[PDB]
Image (cartoon, rainbow, N blue to C red):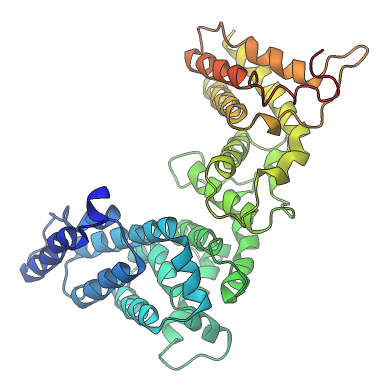
Length: 400
């Protein structure tokens, strides 16, 4: 990456030749390691146009494995641009640029022609969305009557996407694929300042209600087919929704309840752990908007601690409690104030809320069964002793 910020032409010359070579061969070849360099090279808006234009010309003549390879890499290159240059992504909606829209639209049709079977469709849907977003006007036209061919192809794309997301279609593959695709659309929306308030925001609201019913449904958890539930997918969904409408979060409570599975409790404690440590854009909501929930989190740290020491003295179920506990301790190490708010204060017959938590951490230091938690619980107690965090123990009377 660092070797491509300046000498972009040097790196880009290796890829361009490879595509030409793969065009000549009449037999599909499985050597595409050179194509997959796009995942890493630094990219900019102007440079990103260069990758789209060149790929458009040659995508019609490549082979099956090459065609798939260019798609995935070209899909990941987009997020390197948005992550590193958020500003340029915003301007794309304040001031229209007809050059970017044309490049995205042309590549859209070629990809659509490639996909004809259900299995192929599941592979390309996550990319096309990223392209339809780049040409804002085509989205608006779909709302009204549809041109014969300019936008008829794109309009059919959405209706197929929503139908599969709800689950009416009899195809598990597409249902899972639509979940992956629509979570990327929500993620990208956050960068748009929404002062434009383009149809993007109105488009997200249409699916957000249908996405959560599919993911945060305790009765029928969403499993790809191998794992009990794809946790990493749910973290992205919950972290992105919070940033859109922080205060009106009715699905924070679903995870925060005690009756919910133990997998949801895992998603909620790592979603909070990204808001704390990964927040570049300023106008996003911050961790302060969650301090009203400190009471529930302390209780969740109570039972989990109780059921982890007790278990060590089902096998799989007990193993879960050790992962949830390890993550909660890492949370205190990042923002202690999230758990030392709304103190209970010392009671005539009951101990305070700060001591109850402080003692819990100590009883993990001398453990030998859990050598990795005992290492983390030491760091947490060493961060609560800093002069900054000592006022929070009891602001009424700290020294005593």
